[PDB]
Image (cartoon, rainbow, N blue to C red; front, side):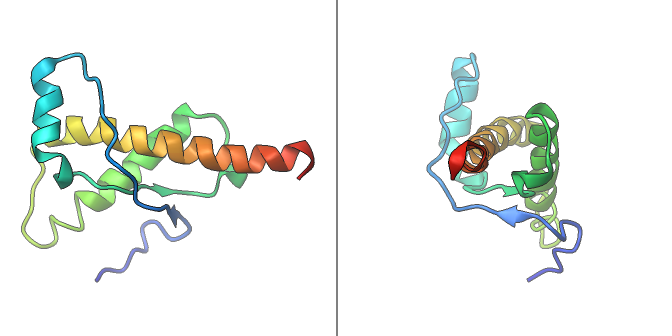
Length: 114
């Protein structure tokens, strides 16, 4: 149990099935796959209601999911080798990319006539 103050006003989505990331290397793909459960199933997003663009959102989502996942463990007895971080950066992006797109679509149906 931890004081999640450094987020403060974020939202934590549902868990989801692992992205398959086509890294372009054969060995990376399997390396991720072999230990893939060591990376999270969820991501932390601010509400899309006060964001703009996708790249900068993608950035700060990574920089909070990875921040938590690399601290909530390195407060117990964990560390993250850079290779873990490369794998995790792609998965953590690929989850929060769909997270934003889904909540974007919710807000854009609002823009329609909903």
